[PDB]
Amino acid sequence: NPIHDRTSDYHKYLKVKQGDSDLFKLTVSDKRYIWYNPDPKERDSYECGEIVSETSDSFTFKTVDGQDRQVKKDDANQRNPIKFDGVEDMSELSYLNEPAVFHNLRVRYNQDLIYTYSGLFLVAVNPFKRIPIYTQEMVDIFKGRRRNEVAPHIFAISDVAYRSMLDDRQNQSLLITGESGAGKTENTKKVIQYLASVAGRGVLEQQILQANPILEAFGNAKTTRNNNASRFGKFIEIQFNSAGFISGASIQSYLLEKSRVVFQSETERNYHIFYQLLAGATAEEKKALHLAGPESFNYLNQSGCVDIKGVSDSEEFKITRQAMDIVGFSQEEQMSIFKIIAGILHLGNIKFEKGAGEGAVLKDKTALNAASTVFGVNPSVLEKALMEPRILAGRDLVAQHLNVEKSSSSRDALVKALYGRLFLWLVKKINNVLCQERKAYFIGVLDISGFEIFKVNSFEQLCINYTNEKLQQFFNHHMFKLEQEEYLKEKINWTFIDFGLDSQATIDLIDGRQPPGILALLDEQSVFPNATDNTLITKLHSHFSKKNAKYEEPRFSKTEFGVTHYAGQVMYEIQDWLEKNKDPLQQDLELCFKDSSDNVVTKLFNDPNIASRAKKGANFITVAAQYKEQLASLMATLETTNPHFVRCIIPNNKQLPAKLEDKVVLDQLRCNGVLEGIRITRKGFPNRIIYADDPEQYRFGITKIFFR
Ligand SMILES: Nc1ncnc2c1ncn2[C@@H]1O[C@H](COP(=O)(O)OP(=O)(O)O)[C@@H](O)[C@H]1O
Ligand SMILES: Cc1ccc2c(c1)C(=O)[C@]1(O)CCN(c3ccccc3)C1=N2
Ligand code: VO4
Ligand SMILES: [Mg+2]
């Protein structure tokens, strides 16, 4: 039994190491200790001080340099007896305070124990290095074990949800939270791994796992926060039959950050797939697609970074191609996929310049021709569609002649639409393959793009961060609000506790209905024919400045507004919001591509599930309305499941192992509600059954007995 055998890999990598006689002496000491701030300005840097005396309301303790200070007992953060250091579930701590919780995660992390319970949910602190705890033999150990029978692990909460699904006949969800780079995506993959192994009886299982490298190659990119940042969110339904065997899966994908295809900030990359193609293509792929190196392509040569530390793009391309094979994409489908990737790189190299008059011309047609060739479209039709698109003016049909900037933006709009529709097509193709059985039950794993702050935050960052704020609201509603409403509806002598975490004011600012929040005002300005980015920001300032406590009109800029999110204030730059929200694409460009000789390109443009834009009145649904609809669908789905939460925690902002930064971590423990979440578990009454069915508590409700 590896659990009990101190020499096992399980003990070695998932259990706290045996302490020594030196540590035993320290563990039986009668001394008592306190966590204090050497520097009072610096509330998250703590040292340990010995308590040397006390009065009825105070402690005097020594400082590290030896001096002595005094603190009111009411303000004191006591250090737990050290026997608690490394404890597996923090609800067991005698003293529950910020530096003690952090210290416990510190002890575990220092020994590469990244998983720790904090009551009913799991905390996972990213190691930023590989740790051998996800092998088949680890899986085998966890299979079927109750949570208190085994060490903290993502496998354990996965097993717990899987047994609840069987035992209760109820759909489950695993909600993995965290800011960008914290570990959501990696933990999500472990959940799927685990569920596929323990509920497996095996092609379908391979196809479920091989979905991932395809989605990541096209949907992930290096940002300044994560070398493998998810730029789309997803909810993965793992499907089971009444017997509990896996019977299929379905991937709900959420809006992709398609602006990254045409622009990346300094040090960032475009989507991985562009680098994988250029590094891994054969000699004949490269010639047939007219490819060169990333440096030759405007969409890859602007950020100054074309490589990621520790990643071989040609190796990843082999893995993406093998995943495509396993999932079932044909050889011609694959070649079409790569033609669309190459063609986008060619479109980006088109250089418009100013003609005799205001209208643009194309004097060098090399990149236009190369694109047209791989796309299987007519280069004259394409050129005309870029620079002289036809529109209605009243009912008249009028050929425009766009200037360089407008031609360039239309070219960029076409590229983003090609790439976003290709992505949707990939997901649709994958799903039809995994759609093999009607499900009896599902466990849904949610992996959103995590909370993110850049030097410049745009409309995509606001939607990301709102998603994160809603997810945090959901944790709060499940841990605190619904928990206490149950106590109240049952009358068990409970005084309501204000846990002081309420995202509602920030949610209403962003998405409120009356008064209108930011998104409703954005939609308003989006169908107002005279609107500009500047009238938009003036309208936000007029509604919220010095009226809404979560909004700030900054004095240092006329083009930014601040939103105080649960995870910190973010300043958003309003430039391009109206164009991003309307997401226009000239119809003459669609007509050009509907005519493509390529079977995949033709689907992207003729298949209404892919090509069609929904309507509202006589305007295309805006991106904000599409955002809202996706989020409201997710929230509706989660409400039909029993949720389990895993809070991923980033150790620092440099993507380095062995470097836990106190301020970085504590900010997350605070805005995640981790200590509040531990307290509700300690102070409350987690279990309750309609009557039927030594010691003390225990509580009798109007229809249930509740026990702590
Ligand atoms: N359990 C883990 N084991 C090893 N590395 C991890 C783990 N979790 C995260 N990482 C590392 O951190 C990087 C960012 O994690 P990821 O899951 O992509 O973040 P996000 O929360 O943004 O999805 C990963 O590419 C991997 O290098
Ligand atoms: C439930 C839901 C709904 C919408 C979402 C997300 C999740 C995301 O995580 C993202 O997919 C991450 C990128 N993003 C996005 C991109 C461009 C414009 C708006 C949102 C997102 N929208
Ligand atoms: O860096 V992450 O996958 O939260 O977008
Ligand atoms: Mg991710």
Image: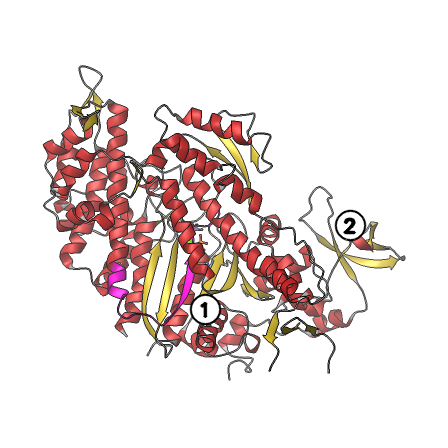
How many numbered callouts?
Answer: 2
Out of 542 and 448, give the one closest to the viewer. Answer: 542
| Numbered badge on residue 132 | 1
Q: Nearer the viewer, residue 111 or 394?
A: 394
Q: Which residue is mark 2?
A: 65
In this view, which residue lies farthest toward the right? Answer: 55
**Compared to 122, does 255 lie above or below?**
above
Q: Is residue 395 left or right of residue 143?
A: left
Identify which residue is drawn at 21% across, 31% down.
350
Which secondary structure, mark 1?
Answer: loop
Q: Quadrant of residue 333?
A: bottom left
Q: Is residue 441 magenta?
A: yes
Q: Quadrant of the C terminus?
A: bottom right
Left or right placement of residue 305 versus residue 383 in this view: right
Residue 141's spot in the image, x, y percent?
47, 78
Circles 1, 2 touching at the beta carbon (< 8 Å): no
The reply to whether the magenta stretch includes residue 674 is: no
The residue at 43%/49% (across/down) is 226
For label 2, the SS is loop
Q: Is mark 2 within 8 Å of ligand 1?
A: no
* Badge 1 or badge 2: first in the primary sequence: 2
x and y percent of residue 677 in the render? 62, 60
Q: Residue at x 18, y 38 (%)?
A: 590
Q: Is residue 484 left or right of residue 544?
A: right
The stretch of residues the image draws in magenta is 430-451
